[PDB]
Image: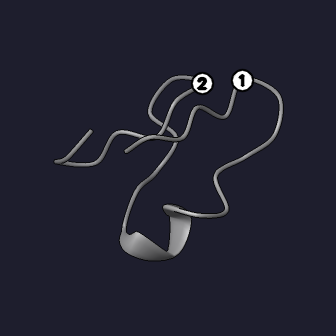
Amino acid sequence: CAESCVWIPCTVTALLGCSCSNKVCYNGIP
């Protein structure tokens, strides 16, 4: 997922099924 929650949490890919694994959204897909 093209979303890194370094400061701000995922909002775009959040509804796509991506969770913050480690300051970046990575759930199956990048």
Mark 2 vs mark 1, CA separation in Å:
5 Å
Residue 3 picture location, percent across and down:
54, 41
User: Regarding mark 1 in the picture, which secondary structure is present there?
Assistant: loop
Q: Residue furthest bottom?
A: 15
Q: Which mark is residue 6?
A: 1
Q: Give the quarter of the figure containing the C terminus.
A: top left
Whichever of callouts 2 and 1 sits on the residue coming sooner in the sequence is 1
Q: Quadrant of residue 12?
A: bottom right
User: Regarding mark 2 in the picture, which secondary structure is present there?
Assistant: loop
What residue is at 67 percent from the left and 62 percent from the top?
11
Q: Residue furthest right?
A: 7
Q: Do the numbered discs 2 and 1 sit on residues whose CB atoms are within 8 Å?
A: yes
Indicate the amino acid at tag 2: Lys
Mark 2 — residue?
23
Residue 2 picture location, percent across and down:
44, 40
What residue is at 81 percent from the left and 40 percent from the top?
8
Binning the other alpha carbons within 10 Å of mark 2 as few (below 14), some (14 to 19) or many (20 upward) gives some
> Is residue 9 toward the left or the right of residue 27 in the image?
right
| Relative to 4, residue 15 above or below | below
Indicate the amino acid at tag 1: Val
Residue 5 picture location, percent across and down:
67, 34
